[PDB]
Length: 102
Image (tube, rainbow, N blue to C red; front, top):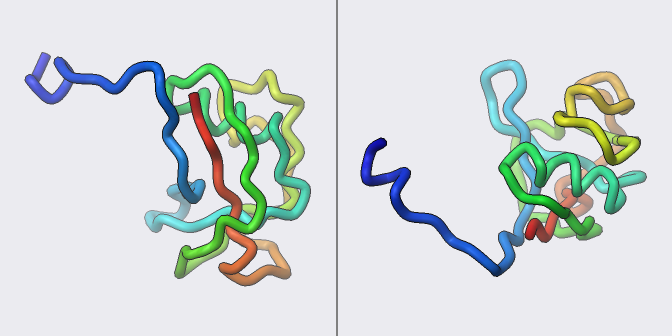
């Protein structure tokens, strides 16, 4: 491993705006229907075991890629979740969803 893989942060929280990489650009997730099940799926992708949804975390820019995300909670990826068409939203970045992963 690189040295970069020989450090880690344990027993705390990673909290912030949830972003997703689609069509070669980072974009954000509207908080419409964004819930703990969605947050857990998102956080699982980063190797965490639980996510809590933070409504209207805000602060993003550019594309809003996802809206009305409706995960069962058991998906390995947001790509497996039911949601609006990618890039189909009626949102602004004040509504950008966040997560507290742990």
